[PDB]
Structures are given as C-alpha cells and as structure tokens.
Length: 315
Ligand SMILES: COc1cc(N2CCC(N(C)C)CC2)c(-c2cnn(C)c2)cc1Nc1ncc(Cl)c(Nc2ccccc2P(C)(C)=O)n1
Image (tube, rainbow, N blue to C red; front, top):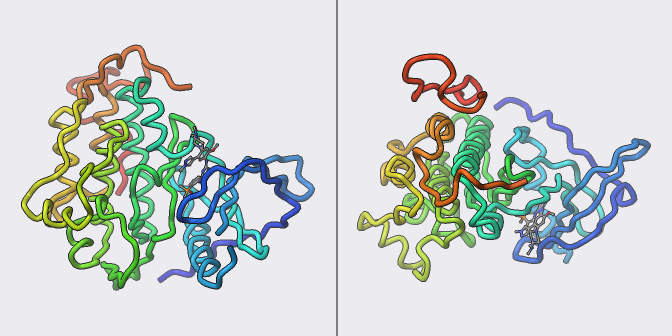
C-alpha cells in the first residue's frame, strides 16, 4: 500500500483541563474538558478517553489512535492527539449533543423528516470515506454516531475498525464480544467482514433512526437472531416509513452481500429523498418542528426528481 504519513500529536497533561465525566461503560470512561494548546490564544472543547493500567488496555487504545489519526472527513471523528500518562488518554473533539441514539429518543417529538434523511446522507458519506481509506468499521450503530450540531453528525468508535490491503477483500475475525443485532449474516456465521457487511449495519442504523430509537429485534436473545435471518425475516417497516425508504433498508439486508447497495449509492438515494422529505417520511407535525429557494428540487426546469448535486455524486 501507500505510506501512512499521518502525524501523531502527543499532548502535555498541563495543556488540557478535565471538567466532567461523560460516560462510564465497557470501553473506559470519557470526560468533557478544555484543551489550551501551548502559546496559542485558543481554547478547544475536547473529550478525553482512557481505560486501570493493563498492557492489553494500552495496546487496544493505541490501535484506535492509529486508525483515528489516519482518517480526515467532516463525517468521521478525528483524533486531536494522545497524552502519555500512566493510563494513555485519547483526545478527540467534543460532540456537545452526545450520541445519535440518545438524541433521537430524547427529542422523539421534535425531529422532522429533513433531519432524519440528512443524518442518513451524512452517515453514508462518512462510511464511503472509510471504504475509500479501505477501513471496515465492524461496529456501525446509532450509539456510534455523535452529534456535533443537530444539523451535523460524525461516525465514532474505531475500537473494532480493520484496514484491508489492496490484495485483501475480507477480514476474518477469530473471537471477541460482537453486537449480533447489527451484524450481517455472513459475519454471524463465517466471521467475514467487508464494506458490504457494514452496509448491513447501516440498514439497522437507519432503522434505529426511523423508529426514533427502538431496539432491533427487541426481547429476542442473540442465539436466536442467526436463525430468524436464515428464514427470510427482517426488521419491521417503521410507521413513518414509506415503502421507498423501507425498500432501501431491506436491500441492505440481502443474503448476497454484492446485491446490497454501496455507500456511494446510499448517498445519492437519501439525497434525492432529502430534496422532498415529506414524500418519503410521514411524521405527524413535520411542517412545525425545530432543533437549534436553495433547498428543494424545484429550481428552474422539468422533472428534477433525479437531480443530485456534485457533492453527493461520489465515484
Ligand atoms: C457534552 O458532550 C456529550 C454529552 C453526553 N451526554 C448526553 C446527554 C446525557 N444526559 C442527558 C443523560 C449526559 C451525557 C454524551 C454521551 C452520553 N451517552 N453517550 C453514549 C455519550 C457525549 C458527549 N460528547 C462526546 N464527545 C466526544 C466523545 Cl468521543 C464522546 N464519547 C463518549 C461519551 C460517553 C460515553 C461513550 C462515548 P463513546 C464510547 C461513543 O466515544 N462523547
């Protein structure tokens, strides 16, 4: 492959001040904070992530740092730098609105069709960039999408992300805790992960957003999910979903991974829908909903139903 000439920035403990704890969970912890770089009249809102010092807990964080310092896209979380204290700290940008799962739940009655369809375009842009950089996320879910502003989301959690060689097209995992309700059938039965198994996970992510934060296959144990998907059974059509949006989800869940749409196609599809959002999502209250010419397929010609902007047409 090409040389990865990315720069790993190492930060002084003194340069940044913690403020509050954000989470507890599996991972490590995660704190809110401020980063005042040395001799710069700049104060950067940051999120400091750590793990308890174990040689395995320091190795896993540095592999994540490797991935995060390589990526650079408006819809992908970037690493600001690392701090080399007893316990290694990952310093990333603060996403003041938290994760997208918690946000759809907390704001269930204020989210309109324009917002949902735009997060779908943004998640597909971030995932396409990862496909370009030959990275397989392996953990795409709504909890792993952070909110910078309600109008701007970014993909996070690279703690499972795998890079592929130019003469490599699959990642064969050996073992480890895996979220089964988001996994592709080939991933559950053969431990194979491709960008196309990420497209499956994208389908469940869109489903979580469309159901305003519902749990996929609720009340159904993990051991049973592999069978359900073998029969032909998929997740239900959400109430707000027209058959157009649902057909896209259903395609992300084909048994043949090559039949599923590509992330560049998912961008085009959700972009067209975002130009007339009320034709694709039926939400009670849409016209009067807020979260604190130029944006419709009208403009000046014929049937501009298939009009895509160049920024959405990636190849
Ligand atoms: C003010 O900023 C945040 C506030 C947060 N609220 C949401 C509302 C909550 N009330 C109303 C109950 C309080 C906590 C949260 C948050 C909450 N839950 N989660 C999962 C994240 C997150 C952020 N921002 C933020 N910016 C950057 C990163 Cl990297 C990050 N990470 C993170 C934090 C906690 C747990 C897990 C992670 P992960 C493993 C997904 O990286 N988190």
